[PDB]
Amino acid sequence: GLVKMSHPSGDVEACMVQVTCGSMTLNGLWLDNTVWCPRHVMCPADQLSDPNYDALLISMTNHSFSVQKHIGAPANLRVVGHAMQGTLLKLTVDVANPSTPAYTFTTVKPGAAFSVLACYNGRPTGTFTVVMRPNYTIKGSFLCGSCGSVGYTKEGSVINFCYMHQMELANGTHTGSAFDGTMYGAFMDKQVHQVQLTDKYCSVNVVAWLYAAILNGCAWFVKPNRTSVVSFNEWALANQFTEFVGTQSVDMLAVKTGVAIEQLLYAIQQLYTGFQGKQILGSTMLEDEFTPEDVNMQIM
Amino acid sequence: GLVKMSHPSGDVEACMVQVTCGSMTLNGLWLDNTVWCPRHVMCPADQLSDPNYDALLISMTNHSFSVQKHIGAPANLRVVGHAMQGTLLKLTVDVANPSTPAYTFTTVKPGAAFSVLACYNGRPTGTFTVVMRPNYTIKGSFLCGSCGSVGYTKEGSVINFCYMHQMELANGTHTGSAFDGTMYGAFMDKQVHQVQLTDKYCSVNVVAWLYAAILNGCAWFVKPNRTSVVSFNEWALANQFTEFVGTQSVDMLAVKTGVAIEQLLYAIQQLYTGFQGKQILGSTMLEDEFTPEDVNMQIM
Ligand SMILES: *C(=O)NCCCCCC
């Protein structure tokens, strides 16, 4: 039985700081001599309707930004430079984070999972895992003052930072930016109403879940009929599924079950219409929030 | 929305060590001058079926145990005392963990949630949240070598340690010790087949989940009809639900929504027989792993 699992957050906790600019405050991420944070910390509350972020960064002086580390030994960090990259601020501080881990900045693609450290005013409060939805939103739990919370994956000892939380959309859809500065789904960091695209099922994750079903004895849906990847993907554009892309992780499931990817792509086409009278792993809905890598590590 | 939220795990990560005795190795918890770990580390795998821990304790010296800390400040320690306490070893080491958090030991009750830091050979690898099941088991991801993994809650600055992982019973079903040394559910730490009681739905958590559904505009299941607590509890004995016991946490959700507890007790009796074709908060079955405290926190 699959469980939602996050990465241990300790390494990321040691990098969180609070960033304050005038009356606005939120979270930032302290790596080496750099503090990253969402640029809307520069924007007075009244002016969020549409801000001129270029006409905000010029107005910034040597001491417009204040940075505080709360966790570990409390410290104020003096800001010595300020630059803007996409929807993020890049602030230079005069002390390097002595607990900077080995890290990279990669953007995640829909269907992939990552861990989120939720913070409030530089203090970690909670951690969960999400998958990037095909409409480039995430289904998180973020309350007031959690902007700048950080999403990440980990391979070896290398932290891959992939998300910095920016805003809430509909009732609980959230989005943020990759650390190159680009907002996921080209949403705009303004208090303007923006429409999200329709969500879709993550096909590769549904496939992983059907492999987890087969591994737990649940395999009534497997039949010899096959749908090819290229055929499946043309079907998908019309039926609210993502394109399928294979990975070595999927292949390892197919090798251990003896069931081919193309059989499960056929099955998905049938199960979409309805499960008829049966269940799969206790569910009557398709499940798309577990990845091949999840199934591989948890049902080894 | 409703996300599976865990406590940030940095405080507990800095206390995980590897404990080795003979050919057996597993995880331990380093608090001040004490390292806690499951006592079956003393038992060679052959006599795991019927160990004599009192004899095994006599046959041991301080030199029978080695302890290493792998992550963070990589210091490794000398054992200067050893004792047994229920199903736990209590080793004394000559260095006080300088990263020890403020902490208590408390035993958790069925229905309650706590975070788990899954480790392997003293390296933290994942975190997730479980609830203590009515049959005094938990469902998580505990692969080979995760014995000694630790469960905890956090209140203010104080970590409350409540669980140290001991064994897998059936597939996916796990149990362990409180830090007073007693096994949850009185199971024996022996590779012997033992029978677990039947699991039940935690009624107070199901009710909180329906409240969360109402607060998110999913209320198709709410009727004027009511079942009293006294009468639901008799029904529960016959349908494998726990006794419903209200708390001020539950009362706040009833106040906020205007929907009485007794209306949701009636709805559970109806939804138990099947959701027909309908969904509640993504789900086609009742969810009982969200607590009223958890719902109050995430949804407010
Ligand atoms: C987070 O601190 N604030 C969210 C409001 C920002 C709206 C425009 C990006």
Image (cartoon, coloured by chain):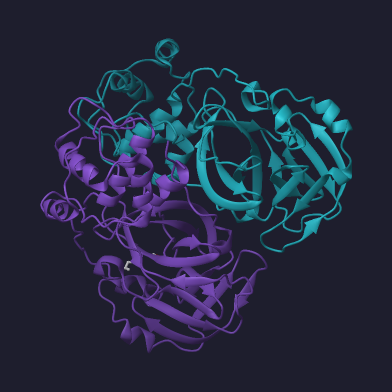
Chain colours: A purple, B cyan
Residue shown at 40% from the left, 45% from the top: A295
Q: Position of residue A277 (x, y in %)?
A: 20, 25
Residue B33 lies, with reference to residue A42, above or below; the image says above
What's the residue at 77%, 55% (across, down)?
B97
Q: In the visual, does A168 lie left or right of B60? A: left
**Relative to A52, residue B139 above or below:** above
Picture coordinates of residue A114 (x, y %)? Answer: 41, 57
Q: Is residue B7 visible?
A: no
- Of residues B286 and B266, which is closer to you in this image? B286
Q: Is residue B143 above or below residue B285?
A: below
Residue B183 in sight from this viewpoint: yes
Q: Position of residue A189 (x, y in %)?
A: 30, 70
If the image is split into quadrants, where does the C terminus of chain B sit? Answer: top left
Left or right of A200? Residue A214 is right
Q: Give the image quarter of residue A265.
A: top left
Ligand 1: quadrant of the figure: bottom left
Measured as percent of width and height from the top left, residue A257 is found at: 35, 40
Pick the residue in front: B256 or A167.
A167
Locate residue A108 relative to residue B278 in the image: left or right: right
In the shown orientation, is residue A267 left or right of residue B113? Answer: left
Count of marks placed on residues: 0
Residue at image position (25%, 34%) is B279
